[PDB]
Amino acid sequence: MQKIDEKLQLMNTIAKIYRGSIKEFNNRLGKLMNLSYLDFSILKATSEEPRSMVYLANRYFVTQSAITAAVDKLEAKGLVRRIRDSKDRRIVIVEITPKGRQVLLEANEVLRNLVNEMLSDVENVEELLEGLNKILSRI
Amino acid sequence: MQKIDEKLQLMNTIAKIYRGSIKEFNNRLGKLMNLSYLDFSILKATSEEPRSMVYLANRYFVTQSAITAAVDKLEAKGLVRRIRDSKDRRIVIVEITPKGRQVLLEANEVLRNLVNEMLSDVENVEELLEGLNKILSRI
């Protein structure tokens, strides 16, 4: 286990964390709010400002098909709506609705407490955050 | 963005890293070796010693159905074989084959170089590794 192997192990561990955490995330949000983790991500990004479908797939590393499927349900629930870009009606834009903003607050609370509960004794979060952000940019 | 939010963001980033890296991992191993990332994981674990199906699903956080599907292909390719536990024939054990050990060496090389190439300028790997391992245990 020299350094050459440490980076791959870093990725092996990240893989496990995602698989394990996503199951918990989807279970919690699914049973309490009938939402998925991706649903939460879309609501968060659009709460910032309207986002195109391409922007969403790009930011969350999912296929446009995955984004479209998620948005279909979110829009049906009245949490977001699709509108055309007013400067290029060729682009589909996702805008959050007032109801969506309210649901996001609740979903954020659910996920934040869940993660806080689980990682209560984890220190050096800030440093881990910078390391992970850099890794993501290199991916 | 107080500390209360940092841990959730840590998970949001990990989610992206997995989605992005797994696509690259599966693409690379798939096109070069007709293997998946999970295939690599199973080969690595069994190269250590024969492992039960439950052990594999547990270690890699995937369903037993996912493990079974992967093993079906691996065994068909002659990379592993399923045998009964000699002390409890009720348990299915996965044993790596000589061919499997050879393929693992190649898959390891492919993934190691790929990750090394991508994360070449990432420092503080050891510390990130400890942090991530602790997080995984808490999940």
Image (cartoon, coloured by chain):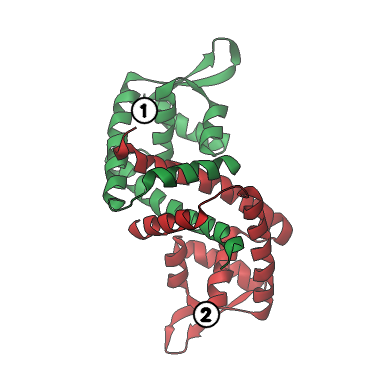
Chain colours: A green, B red
Q: Which residue is mark 1?
A: A77
The picture places residue A91, in percent across and down from the top left corner, at: 58, 19
Q: CA distance from mark 1 to mark 2?
A: 50 Å
The picture places residue B92, in percent across and down from the top left corner, at: 47, 78
**Label 2: chain?**
B
Q: Nearer the viewer, residue B32 or A129?
A: A129
Q: Amino acid at mark 2?
A: Glu
Image quadrant of residue B10?
Answer: top left
The picture places residue B110, in percent across and down from the top left corner, at: 68, 60
Quarter of the rendering occupied by the N terminus of chain B: top left
Q: Are marks 1 and 2 in contact (CB under 8 Å)?
A: no
Q: Is residue B15 visible?
A: no
Q: Residues within 10 Å of mark 2 (few under 14, many from 20)?
A: few
> Which residue corresponds to the image point at 39% horizontal and 43% vertical from the top-left?
A126
Q: Which residue is mark 2?
A: B49
B112 lies left or right of B52: right
> Which residue corresponds to the image point at 42% horizontal and 34% vertical from the top-left?
A41
Q: Amino acid at mark 1?
A: Lys
